[PDB]
Image 1: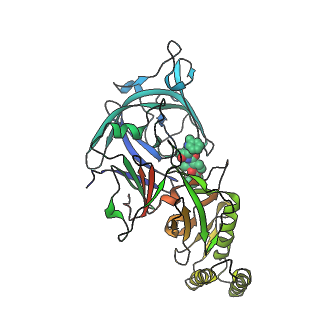
Image 2: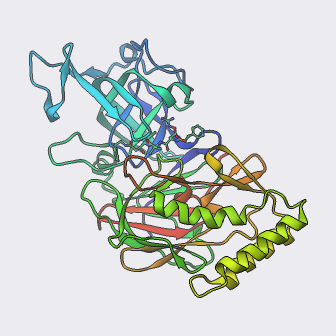
Length: 395
Ligand SMILES: CC(C)C[C@H](NC(=O)[C@@H](NC(=O)[C@H](CCONC(=N)N)NC(=O)OCc1ccccc1)C(C)C)[C@@H](O)CC(=O)NCCc1ccccc1
């Protein structure tokens, strides 16, 4: 019975490698496309002075054309929020995990968020103008980035806290529901009607106050626990991470099983049979649920589910059929099912593994953990929810 405001998301894993939405900024409104990013806190984009940025769907935001825009000046005053002051403006800067360094200056202006059912919420936000962009940002259709994390006590008020402060008719919950193509952002709750069958939401406490981290205790495949370490892994729930990132030790164990499932020479029956026998020797023992492993192999072989490899040895199958579920054990020791229609993504006519080794010791639950689920950010109760869903698609 909760009031829900719904926003269209566009995007995919293979071609965009993010999901984005449109927002209005300034007076009169300027439509701007933003990467939906629960892994950062800012709202930012190029602005018209920019001489070192990338080309995007929209022209850089034009400050002179917004009657309500206001650049944040300093060095005749102090920069609030402990920001740097360079050449008289409060400096915007962000280092991202992928390696991008984005810098510029801060300004505030009116933000208008409008649902596709014409429900409008409007407020001023302190936003960053990109004056320098880098690397992946130079090859990106989306114009800017919309961080969805929470405000710190003496920090910049973020989009999400502002949205709810100016929309008291909504409960402080946002849900991301991504498909292979586009998806949906919901403010005010989740939609039970999208839920598969009717399946129940699996809840976890967030492990840090202003960021979306949860603990993962185990990661099973064919009945084998691949996590070697005792402390649960603290993983960022990040819609701005194309893939799910895991430790090397963990990745290599999973990848060993995925390598065997990846048969690149089905035309070669002799070599296939050799793989089968090699697999029976190696894994027909109590360390593995061998039944399921052979079940998976036979399915893959019977349906001629050919595999090919792409960059860094990532495996791509013709079909989802035959691939096993992975099982994620969360904090309260719930064993959650991670299906191939999530951890594999569509690339051309194949389904490719959306799991990588981590960089900088940062484990991340990325879009391949969001896909075909409702991921529910219950800000009020400090928890994140997961449930299998038929998410909307765009286009
Ligand atoms: C939009 C993006 C820059 C947001 C950022 N995500 C990331 O940095 C991740 N980036 C990715 O997954 C990127 C995002 C998409 O491309 N990036 C872009 N256009 N700018 N994907 C990506 O590299 O996949 C490669 C690719 C590129 C093109 C086509 C197909 C595949 C890293 C982890 C691999 C954010 O979610 C995490 C972050 O760095 N936040 C900064 C604050 C912080 C710092 C440390 C920990 C937690 C938070």
